[PDB]
Image (cartoon, rainbow, N blue to C red; front, side, top):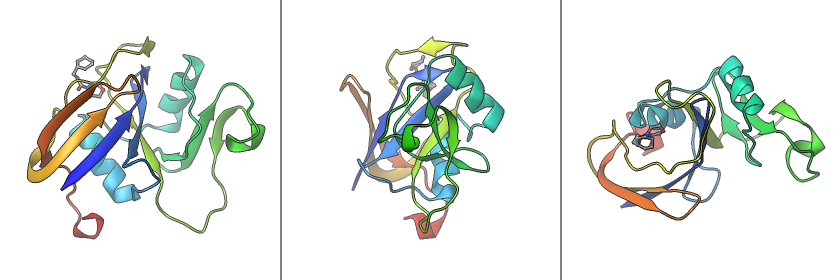
Length: 150
Ligand SMILES: O=C(CCC1CCCCC1)N1CCOCC1
């Protein structure tokens, strides 16, 4: 009973979270997952400020109201070579990664590692935070509040 959560740098408090190395989070699970990091789904304004500070990924993830990819450098295989906060318009499917926003993070680029899952609740799952540099933090708990996500 294990969940891997790959996390990034925080940019103006915004960061990316990928679950189990594949697109696998529903919108309900995404809000619960950010709450476990004492965080919320970013607003579009919060995401645009994060982009302006250096944030980009090559993965679709939820924000409040949309599924997006923040892009700085054009790349043909990331958001069809677009720049800016690219918004997914047409998809058949419902599961993506998520973005999260923590208001207490530093104002600009924070590329230190994540060393805690501060607001997870009691549960049976071994949850492992995996940083880009490979460092890990594990703790037993749960974050999902909706049965359909378990
Ligand atoms: O776990 C924590 C805080 C513990 C430490 C405290 C300083 C920042 C690095 C790690 N967070 C989860 C998601 O990003 C914002 C905060």
